[PDB]
Image: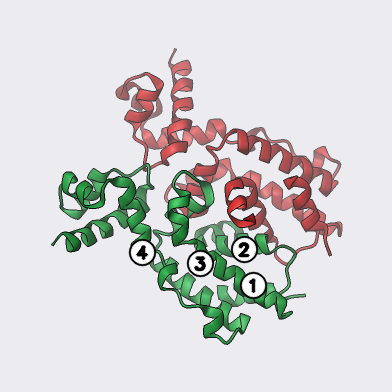
Chain colours: A red, B green
Amino acid sequence: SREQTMENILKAAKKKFGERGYEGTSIQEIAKEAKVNVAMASYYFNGKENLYYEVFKKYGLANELPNFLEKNQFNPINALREYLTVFTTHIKENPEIGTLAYEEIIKESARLEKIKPYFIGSFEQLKEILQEGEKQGVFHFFSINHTIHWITSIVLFPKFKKFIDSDLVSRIISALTDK
Amino acid sequence: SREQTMENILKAAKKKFGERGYEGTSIQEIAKEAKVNVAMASYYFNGKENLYYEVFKKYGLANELPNFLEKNQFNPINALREYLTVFTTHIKENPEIGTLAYEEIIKESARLEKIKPYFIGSFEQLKEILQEGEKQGVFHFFSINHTIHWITSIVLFPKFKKFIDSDLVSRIISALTDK
């Protein structure tokens, strides 16, 4: 069926886009990887750019993410522990956010507005947790922005952690709570 | 002459690699951009991978970077001011470090060891300045690592600054000196 095929194409697309980035990947490489022809792939998704958006729309974590504050009765340490655990485990297991979050959030712009709706929640929530923590007097920081900056970096990019340095959840909590 | 031609190819390569990343760019695209043929390009640089290293070796800033501490008589504020100014101006004017520092330092590994020698000095120096500042009691921070993490991010990636937030040298100095 068209839908099942489209699921196979998306899986192939996550892989190739994760490898080469948007501008580095052709619909042909994805079609080859999916064992379908280009015209079919292009028809089903209405082109490479929509196919790319569909990868975020299918594999983006935000849509199915619980509200961690609410789930933890607004305990900002428990909420943050749960949030970081959910993230670090998923990111190591799927390092196609490594390349694609970098390209689109960190470096760039062109397609930004189209994909934002699929990662901005993850950031809005981290911000909520840090600010609820600050409000409750348990977290301390100069800039919410830099804190967001540095938490993101060390979570998304564990090999850059290595480059510098040369578990993580508890390390982040300890940094935040220090006075 | 072979050398002049190679300079034209390198300029073309900085551009295309900056656009599409290593795995996203072919020697053919660079050859086309340079108005030479592929065999010549490939012969002159001994292949795409060496050509890539040559881009770092030619456009990497570290090799011609002064020692900012020494230049500023070991005043860590003046040194850091000068270091950040040199960096932010060069990075905005050449956003082919944006993509290539991300790909190689931040995300990845494969070719890491080959290119490190061409950016590790920039990081070693920032570290020196921050630590000399800390030693002299003027800079205050929990983790030298996170500080390196967050300074890098907001300097390299000004559009991610915007995504979050939604001049810089003085902002960084002020964050560091606060107690």
Q: Earlier in the sequence, mark 1 or mark 4?
A: 4
Residue A35 tag number: none
Q: Chain of mark 2?
A: B
The residue that disc 1 covers is B130
Could one spot residue B149 in this view of the protein? yes
Element under disc 1? helix
**Label 2 element class:** helix
Name which residue lies at 70% across and 61% down.
Answer: A144
Callout 2 crowding tier (Cα within 10 Å): few <14, some 14–19, many ≥20: some
- Of all residues shown, which one is farthest toward the bottom? B73
Numbered disc total = 4
Question: Which disc is residue B148 wearing?
Answer: 2
- Which chain does tag 1 point to? B
Looking at the picture, does residue A138 appear above or below residue A55?
below
**What residue would you read off at disc 4?**
B59
Give the CA distance from mark 3 to mark 2: 11 Å
Residue B153: image quadrant is: bottom right
Nearer the N terminus, badge 3 or badge 4? 4
Mark 1 in CB contact with mark 2 (< 8 angstroms): yes
Question: In whole angstroms, how far apart are the C-alphas of marks 3 and 4?
Answer: 13 Å
Give yes or no for contact between labels 3 and 2 (Cβ–Cβ under 8 Å): no
Task: Give me the C-alpha separation between circle 1 and circle 2.
Answer: 9 Å
Instruction: Say which amino acid is labelled 3.
Output: Ser
